[PDB]
Structures are given as structure tokens and as C-alpha cells.
Image (cartoon, rainbow, N blue to C red):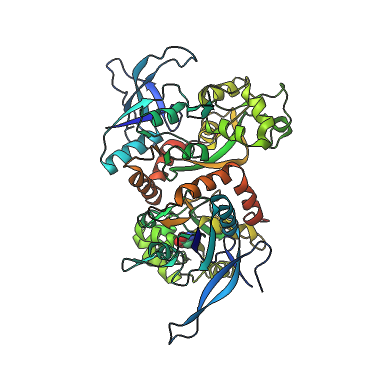
Amino acid sequence: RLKIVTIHQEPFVYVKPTLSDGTCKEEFTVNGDPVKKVICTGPNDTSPGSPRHTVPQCCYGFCIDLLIKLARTMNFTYEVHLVADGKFGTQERVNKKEWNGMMGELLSGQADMIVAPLTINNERAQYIEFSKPFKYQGLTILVKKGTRITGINDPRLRNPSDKFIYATVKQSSVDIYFRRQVELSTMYRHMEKHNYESAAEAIQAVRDNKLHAFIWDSAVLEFEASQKCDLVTTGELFFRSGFGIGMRKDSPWKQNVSLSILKSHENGFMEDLDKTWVRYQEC
Amino acid sequence: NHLSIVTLEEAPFVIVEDIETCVRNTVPCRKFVKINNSTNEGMNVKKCCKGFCIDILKKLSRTVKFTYDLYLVTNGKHGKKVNNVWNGMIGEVVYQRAVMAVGSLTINEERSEVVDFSVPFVETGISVMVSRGTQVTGLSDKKFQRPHDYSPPFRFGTVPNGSTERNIRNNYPYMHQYMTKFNQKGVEDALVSLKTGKLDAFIYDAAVLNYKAGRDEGCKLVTIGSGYIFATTGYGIALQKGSPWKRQIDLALLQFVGDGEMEELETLWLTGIC
Ligand SMILES: N[C@@H](CCC(=O)O)C(=O)O
């Protein structure tokens, strides 16, 4: 019975309360099919430095459908939980270094597999096994409709001031990316003061004119812009990256997880998930 | 430390030139050339190789710390399983003639059963090239799926024996059997067929098609959709199963992506005027 760790990240992972009886509300997809939901335990209010009260919740979305497909293909059972600290995972200095987020849970044995929109990168690949990518995407910039920014090389990003605020999500692949590239140090120092605990909080802050630009995954940002017409993406993709399933290096499932993902791209299953969860709406 | 590496010409990933040494952005690469067809005798002609994948190989050689003897495959091309035996670059790796295969080598499920692939280093998949304005939705378009429902039927093909034909054969049996009369011997023949009106569409590797549309004279030939890709995958370095080289090659490729070294290679080799 595999312990699966995930994270709230629409449209990949939706997280909703259970009904009073502890079951999940019956719903249908955009195509009329029943939505497959799983019980996922996790903390409720994610306020930093506070105690975490774990409660059963309902999880569904692209990554949950992918998990169900992996479980049926490879004949394994599982139990899903939401990452306790609500983060994707970075390695921070404490000489000693430690991993937080889903990366920390997988390496400590709190999870056996990460099934989420987890970016494949050098830093994490030294410690864990990533599958071949289940999604190819990159980074883009989300702004309020009307905000004029050319992209990553715009002077309001490259020569920053407190008049135009931009940020990413703390302890994420975007935070890793900006901290590693010396040429991005000017931007990293600006963002460090303004980074958000979660993508949802950052997206809301762009809608509320509290954050002028949010730098994040195009797979998420393009979805948000397709749903909220006051939100737009700007500029070409940069840091073209993919999402992969994460496992420990000694996992007996690693070869078959990657073969299953390749099979899914090739037979149209991955495109079926894009049509169900990602590309069905337009602004 | 000194590794036998196999490649295959496919511009701009691997471009072959005549040699009396290899200079500039080129590396030595040999090609076995037959003396005649009534002998097994041949000679290893010294040639020079360059391109996106050659630049990747140079970076890996330096970072991972290996030297190599690069050769061009002569038994087939990228890789096909024929009577259960792999030929092409895949075959060279399977049958341990090469430690690794570097080139425009698509990662797919059946190849991953016999070789280990590195992380993908170029995004690809299956795209469709048409003359600008051709109305085709994607691979699921009825003009492709049920071709004889149209009078006259749509004329489309691929270059057989690669990952694209294998995908079409497995997914769309009627389309596949219809298409084989439009098989193109190579990408250059297919582009000529499209430009002279002998073909309506050409289905092939997305990365090569995007590169060709980028350089098309007059920018007449385009890939359908927003440069739409079915069965998104990538090119990968093929290694022997259980290779001790995979771990460090993967970390190095991921380091290059993370340091923006891949975007530079894309600008240098792939982006076109169109
Ligand atoms: N890159 C392909 C060859 C071209 C194609 O079939 O699209 C392969 O590795 O087979």
C-alpha cells in the first residue's frame, strides 16, 4: 500500500472538504463523465508556524486521474495525503542541509511516491528518481489584464523597484531556478521579499492588485487565464521544464511508472486528461 | 572512459561534412562505407560531425569526463524492431556496439523496454506539416482517420520505420494502411512533395518539422495548430540497460537546462526566420 503525497494545485489537484458523512460530492466532468475522487488527508488552515490539524478531504484532477491509471496498470493500492508543510520542496541550509515539502516527505519515508505537478530539475534528481515527464511545460508570467510587461526581460523585472512587485511561490522549483542563476540574482533579491506560501494565494493577489506579476508554471497559469478573464499570461516560455512522478532511487516501481507514462502519451490517454482538466475553456 | 558512441545524420541535430582533420565546431565521426555489394568489406571513412546533438555530446564529454569514438549508424536509421531484432541506433546500443546513441532519437515505450534513455533534452512528438491555411485539426481529423470519406481523399504520409510510423500503426490502423502509398524516403523528398502539390500533409517528428517550417522559403509550410504536438516526448540519449553512465548524464543534461545552456543551443541551431 503506497503512501502518495500530493499538493493542492488546480487543475492538477483540486482539494475540497468532504461531505458531513465523510464521502465526496458526486460530480461530472466537462464531458459528462463521473469525476473520480479520492479521500486525501491533510492539514486545513495552512498558516505558517501554527499546529497542523489533519482531516480527511477530497482530491481530484489531472494528477488524481493519473494516479488511478498508474494504480490500475501496475496493480498497486494506495493512500493519498497532502504535504504537511504545503510546499513542493527545496534543499535549504540549516553546514547541514535538509529537504522540505514533498521532497522531504518522500526522502524521510512519510511518502513512497509524489504524484503532483512536480518539476524535474537537477537539484531534486540528485536525491530522487523522476519518471519521464507526464507533462511538458515551462515558466511564464501572470499579470492583471491591462498590465503591460513584455516578458522576463522587461525593465520592470530586470531593473526592479518597489513600484512594480513580482514574486513566485516559496520553496518551489521557481525559487530554486532564480536562486541558482547568477544572471537572475537581481530578480531573486526582489522576489525573496514578496514570495507567497502557495500559488492560489499569489494568483488571488494578482486579481486583487496586491502583486503585479506572478512567475510560475505555464500549465497552471494558462489554465487560470483560460478561467479568469481579468488574468493574462505574458511573454514566451522560459525554463522549459516537465513534471514527473517522484520516487526513492530504490523504488521497485520506477521502470514501470516511466513505461506507463510513455504508453499514456503515445495512446492519447495524456491528451484525454488535457481535454478533461486543462484545455476546455477560453477567455 | 573511452566510449563507442553512435549517431545518425538529421539536420540540424547532426550534420555530416567532409574532413586533413576536423576543425571549428565539428568533431570527428566515422562512417563504414562498403567497397561493393558482393563483399562484406568496407572502410571507415573519416568525416566531421556538427549540430545541436554534437554540441550536447561535447558538453557531456567535458562535464561527465569521458572521451569518445563517434560513428554513424549504417544498419538502418533511428531504430526499428524487425522480426524481434532492433536495427538502427537502438540496435547498436542493444547489441553493445555502442555505449550510447546521440542524435534525434525519440523516446518511446517500446525502445525504453530494451535501452535506458536519459532525461529528454529536446521536446518533440508528432506534428503535421501543411501549406499555410490547410484546414486540419490534428491526427484525429476525419481527413486522416477515414480518408476515403473525402472525394478526392487527402494525400498524406510520413517517413517510414521511425517512431512516428510506429505510433500511427499502433493507434490508427486504417489511416496507417492508407498512408503507406504516400511513404516519403526522407524529409527533403517530403518537403518537395508538399511544395509541388503532390502531398497535402506530412506527419513527422515535431522538432524537425518546427525547424523546417522556420527555414521554409517564403514561409509557406507550417505545422498545424499553435505548432500542436501529439504524444509529447523528447529526444533522449540511449544507454545500455543498467548503464553506470546514466546517473551523471541525466544530472549534466538537467544542469544544462537549469543554467540556460539549452536555450543558447536552441537559438544557435533551431530558431528560423519564419
Ligand atoms: N526521431 C524519430 C525519427 C523520425 C520520426 O519517425 O518522426 C525516431 O527516433 O524514430
Quarter of the picture holding the C terminus of chain A: top right
In this rendering, position of residue B39 left or right of residue B12: left
Relative vertical location of residue A152 with respect to residue B176 in this rendering, above or below: above
Question: Which is more toward the observer, B155 or A130?
Answer: A130
Who's the residue at 48% across and 14% down the image? A47
Please provide percent x and percent y for residue A105.
Answer: 40, 28
A223 displayed left or right of A63: right
Q: Is residue B25 visible?
A: yes
Residue B222 or residue A158, whichever sits in front: A158
The residue lying furthest to the bottom in this view is B38
Q: Is residue B180 left or right of residue B52?
A: left
Residue found farthest to the top = A50
A237, above or below A13, in the image? below
Q: Position of residue B29 (x, y in %)?
A: 56, 68
Residue A253 lies, in percent from the top left, at 32, 42
Whether residue A151 is visible: no
Which residue does the image show at 27% across and 16% down from the upper left? A21
Front residue of B177 and B231:
B231
The residue positioned 47% from the left and 72% from the top of the image is B74
Q: Quadrant of the N terminus of chain A?
A: top left
